[PDB]
Image (cartoon, rainbow over all chains, first blue to last red; front, side, top):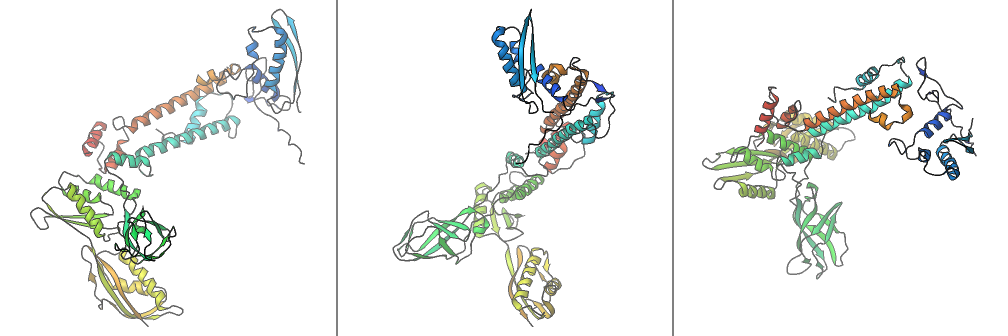
Length: 120
Length: 346
Length: 78
């Protein structure tokens, strides 16, 4: 009968995702609220695999870096990477679902469009 | 040093060691995480201090102390079980085989000898206590109950009091023995070595050794029970036989036990309202018992009078006499005061 | 330096380096304290712990030397 309790706003440090270095506002890390914490969490999860570092929990980590280095053809690894991203990102309770649109083949650089569904 | 590092000092050191362009204030997230890490580190330091204490085992009792004492050669004397004989009363011809279990109250006992009721071997069979402890030293004429019901057996009683139930060792007694040995500078063939031999025997709380009591090659050995009490003849026999096993051959050793001194109390005391003779008599018995436990030297007639008047239900007393006299009686060596006759009237 | 190696690559900034350097200095202090305590466990390697050894021996003597204290402890036993 009682309704589900809403997840409280996730607050933590902030920085520019392109800078990859923490930023300080007059000595205070920038506050992240609403759709600010989930981007940081996804960036942290995707950027580094757990199996490289013993400290992280086993559920953490992604296996997209296995596809790095051209270990298999693109045709099936497109769907394989979609599934890998889905496994790596839906572990977060905040995130509801993740959708992958397609992949673009050009030279050696692969570009893909992936979608994120959130609560707030 | 574990004690040198403390909570706030290491907290401040951790805060200071890192140079921050960020101002540090109370309640800050950085301050909060430093506080949590400092709490965990202080827990670790307290655990290290506790481990050091365990290593030196100064205050707290643990297996480290017992093992170190065993390294030094002193052994924890667990004790001996009480022994006695009981009488089986019932139908003739019933056979009580070995290992038969008999229970008196919570205490449990086992029959040692196969006894047949009405046989030519008698109805008495030795019984050994199934556990170590002084509580198993039952008095005579105690009624025992069969755990397993046997047809033709009605009454189980002991013709004599059970003996041999030495108390289980406690850590305090072992520590005291180790400490007194540490003061003792023993030597192969010296009074300290003999008193240590006496300490090896169960129930030897106090040791007294008198050299040259009869002169040439004579040792007088005096032992005491708990709180300077007497020891059973079986304990004395075990102690003397153990000594003779280890003692030098040729010396004469005499082992004795303290003997009680009987007292009789006569007085005329006006009882208070609502108090009967039995209640005040029992209360004064308890008071005089604890006074005797706490006494040293001689029984003081004035202390006796004071401990009687302070008894609840006592209004006015007169002509108080200990053994018919108002004079203090000397309590000599290996002697204790024992209450035998209590005479109170109104 | 251990944690930053265990730490993810994107956290290679100066703040992390400073924090883990301070934590590693604390680790060095803790491990040298542990080594000193383990030395204190043994009679030969103990320096200030001989006081409780003497107390267990139930002999009180003014502090003269660590080697002298150990020799006195050895003489007291057996």
